[PDB]
Amino acid sequence: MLTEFDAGYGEQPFRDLCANYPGAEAYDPHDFRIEWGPIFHRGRLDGSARVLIVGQDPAQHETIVRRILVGTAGRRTQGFLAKLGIVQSYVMVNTFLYSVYGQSGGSKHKNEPGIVDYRNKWFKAVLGPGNIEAVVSLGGLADEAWKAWLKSSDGAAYKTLAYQHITHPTWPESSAHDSATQAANTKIMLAKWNAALAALAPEVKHPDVPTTLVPYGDAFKPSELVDIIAKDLPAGLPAWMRGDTPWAVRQGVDAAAKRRTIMITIPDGVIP
Amino acid sequence: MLTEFDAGYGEQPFRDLCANYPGAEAYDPHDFRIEWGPIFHRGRLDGSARVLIVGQDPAQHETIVRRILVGTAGRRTQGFLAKLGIVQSYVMVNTFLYSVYGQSGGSKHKNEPGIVDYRNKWFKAVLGPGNIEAVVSLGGLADEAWKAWLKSSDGAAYKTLAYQHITHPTWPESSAHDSATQAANTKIMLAKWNAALAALAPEVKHPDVPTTLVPYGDAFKPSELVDIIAKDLPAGLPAWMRGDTPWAVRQGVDAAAKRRTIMITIPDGVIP
């Protein structure tokens, strides 16, 4: 009857970071959903993380849970980590503190000093303890974020840290609306993911569970979509929030209404 | 531009309390909205609280923020504390960890040992440091919770602790839908709140701000409705979540649907 949870940001330097975060002066209020407040991380901040995941930006599930990579992209990422024998020893930060508002917002503000400097303080803080053995970026903007970090003074020390850029987990669904094209692109993505795993496996010297590498097939199997663990969520969050069924969506009759609303629906079967 | 936040539950004894909370074995799954997870407290857990508030049960705003007293009842309670000069030195705990399901009243399970025992652990932890100088209960079930605490072995020590039972903050709106009856019931409520203030004022010897007692009139004035402070909310929560405008509602075509869904709408004016 013992359930774990993420206590959060009480320790330094994370406490000062979360109390002094960038707002509209760095993140444009039209081009970013700053109205939901920042979402900072997911995973270990106690120094026990072995893998750093760099994602892009949060969406509506993250906005409720208050931790990043908690939707479909998150369960695919968890499963990626599982293939390396990593079940809890990771830490995750995003390129952006806030959701990008718009189709291909870019990359339009990736060069904002206020944005990059604050993100670099987080890199600095999570890499600080010196236990991270591998870095994985999800998508191009994350890949650029990591490379820009390496060119900074504090980042110079991490040029030799094992690193893989991999295709963004939801890329197949965003590349086409057609089912057949989604499947074809998924096969392509997983082939590239297999190569990344092969390069990273020998550098993850301290896995949580010693594991022999089992490659992805052409489609995701159910076992490779792994629920986010309780230890990652704030105290008291119900188990279905870290389950396998979608439960939040933006809702509105037009663009402006839709920007203002999230609807949360408990999956069927939880309530008796 | 530092914004404060509640780091939460990382310190003992709270860490073990939040990791070992009661579920369906103590709170009946039909009579309690256990599907949303427990909401534990609001305010100081570092020992600096001077007033303990005992509330009844959480609703939909609390369900999103993950702290108690966050809606209309909370802002009325904040204003009550403000009149005693208490701006941040309070701690609030609920009679029930979960929302009561059904107007029937969760008085049906008020003596269930699983519920009472766990709540007493929270009483013991918050009263432990010995800095609480006054206790206020909101409504009848809360009053019975404090009285049940006093009858237990550990609670015996607090029979001399200054204590006032006051009428639940949202009693006027729950007693009638007629505008004129609400105003009349509000006038009765505020007379009883004024009596409580008079009894508590000389007993709150450590206000955050020394304040001369200004009694309520017959209705709430806007200055007597006080926004929840940033220090009470998890890191990153946007300011409108602790503003003066309602922003969450239960929504569904029928009872079963309504039980499963919360809709969040950002107040107008936050998004440019």
Image: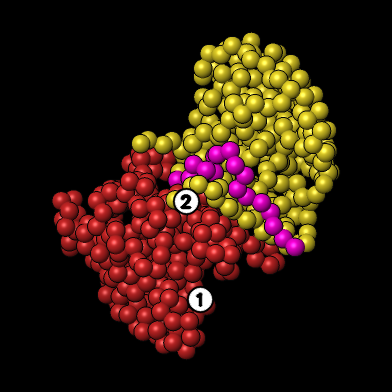
Chain colours: A yellow, B red
Q: Residues within 10 Å of mark 1 (few under 14, many from 20)?
A: few
Mark 1 residue element: helix
Q: Which mark is residue A158?
A: none
Q: Could you tell me residue A89's position as x and y percent? A: 54, 25
- Counting labels gives 2
Please name whichever residue, A270 or A126, is drawn nearer the observer in this view of the structure.
Answer: A270
Report if the CB atoms under discs 2 and 1 are less than 8 Å apart: no
- Circles 2 and 1 on the same chain: no
In the image, residue A16 lies in the stretch drawn in magenta:
no
In the image, residue A252 lies in the stretch drawn in magenta:
yes
Q: Could you tell me residue B247's position as x and y percent? A: 59, 64
Task: Please indicate, yes or no, whether residue B111 appears anywhere in the rendered image.
Answer: yes
Label 2, label 1: how far apart the Cα atoms are? 41 Å
Q: Residues within 10 Å of mark 2 (few under 14, many from 20)?
A: some
The residue shown at (65%, 62%) is B266
Compared to residue A26, the image places residue A73 above or below, namely above
Amino acid type shown at disc 1: Ser
Compared to residue B239, the image places residue A108 above or below, namely above
| Residue range corresponding to the magenta coloring | A236-253
Q: Which mark is residue B223?
A: 1
Amino acid type shown at disc 2: Ile
Q: Could you tell me residue A140's position as x and y percent? A: 79, 31
Image quadrant assignment for residue A138? top right
For label 2, the residue is A271
The residue shown at (54%, 48%) is A268
Q: Could you tell me residue B193's position as x and y percent? A: 35, 77
The residue shown at (53%, 31%) is A44
